[PDB]
Amino acid sequence: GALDVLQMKEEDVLKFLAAGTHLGGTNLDFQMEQYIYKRKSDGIYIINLKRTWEKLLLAARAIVAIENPADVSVISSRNTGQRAVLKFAAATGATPIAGRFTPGTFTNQIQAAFREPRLLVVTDPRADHQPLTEASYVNLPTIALCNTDSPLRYVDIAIPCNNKGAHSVGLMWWMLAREVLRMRGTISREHPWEVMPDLYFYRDPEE
RNA sequence: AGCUCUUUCUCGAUUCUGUGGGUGGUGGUGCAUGGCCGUUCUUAGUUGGUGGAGCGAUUUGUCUGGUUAAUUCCGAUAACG
Ligand SMILES: [Mg+2]
Ligand SMILES: [Mg+2]
Ligand SMILES: [Mg+2]
Ligand SMILES: [Mg+2]
Ligand SMILES: [Mg+2]
Ligand SMILES: [Mg+2]
Ligand SMILES: [Mg+2]
Ligand SMILES: [Mg+2]
Ligand SMILES: [Mg+2]
């Protein structure tokens, strides 16, 4: 937003640079060109943070406008985003899908997995292409976290970030939960949040 | 074989004559058919409902790979059941 209550604070830029979310890929595509600051001395692109923040608050403003919280289905297929989507759906009452997608869940009126969402959030356009291709049949908008080499086909609100590393992905889902819960009422601003981002990170099997 | 011929007793309305019409047939057609059987074919093969691809005949599901006597399973997965 244009305001000052919605502006990025110094405590969040440290969370960003600590998770590494500013660090892009090696290849750029001509649709993500407005989100890049400059290519490093070695071949890697820096993502502009102020632009990440504005696209993240636009996604939150798109999610808050849906009345029933339970038709904002969230999807992750890679192993890094499963815990994050499960915790995001818990914190704000969406319906998560981790693992395989079982094509036809959006367009098949027999299956027991058939639902009719009203939004669609997704971790990675290039790894969860089946939900996008199916959303392209039932008038279904889409929000997506994009790496610097993400194809922006059928996505409607791309959020630029490092999409590869587990810490980055969990931090982005945590911040998306923070800002929907903030502007819906609920956990009012001028307080830190009870949950720490590490509840949202990938497990990466332990000792 | 009263089959027929010579001869002339016996039976009793059941027949006989003619016209229609039936009846029977190990007669014809298995290239008019039912049913049964044999064989393709002793192997692992077949099919539709909703969804996806194609203008369409069609295709996916019914599979790269491993496994099994086996489309038997494990799995992979625009398919689900
Ligand atoms: Mg006859
Ligand atoms: Mg006969
Ligand atoms: Mg015959
Ligand atoms: Mg016959
Ligand atoms: Mg069809
Ligand atoms: Mg068609
Ligand atoms: Mg077939
Ligand atoms: Mg064998
Ligand atoms: Mg299986």
Image: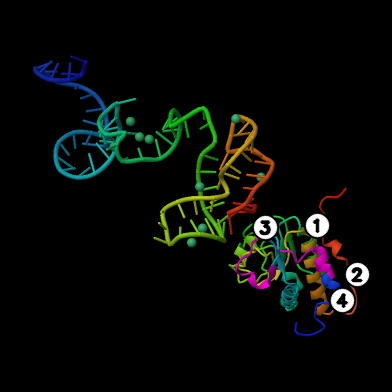
In terms of depth relative to the viewer, which is nearer, A108 or B7?
A: A108
| Distance of label 1 from label 4 (alpha carbons) | 25 Å
First of labels 1, 4 by sequence position: 4
Q: Which residue is mark 3?
A: A101
**Part of the protein shown in magenta:** A14-38
Name, please, the residue furthest toward the bottom: A3
Amino acid under disc 3: Phe
Q: Position of residue B38 (x, y in %)?
A: 44, 28
Label 4 and label 2: CA atoms lie apart by: 10 Å
Say which residue label 4 marks. Answer: A187
Report if residue A48 is visible in the image: yes
Chain ID, mark 2: A
Q: Quadrant of residue A109?
A: bottom right
Pointer 3 and pointer 2 on the same chain: yes
Q: Residue at x 90, y 74 (%)?
A: A192
Element at badge 2? loop
Tag 1 and tag 4 share a subunit: yes
Gap between marks 3 and 1, in whole Å?
20 Å
Q: Residue A26 at what x, y percent from top left?
A: 67, 60
Judging from the image, the colouring scheme is: rainbow
Q: In the image, is residue B75 above or below residue A101?
A: above
- Percent coordinates x, y for residue A207 in the rendering: 88, 48
> Does residue A41 appear to the left or right of A175 in the view shown?
left
- The numbered mark at residue A194 is 2
Q: Is mark 1 within 8 Å of ligand 9?
A: no
Marked residue chain, label 3 = A
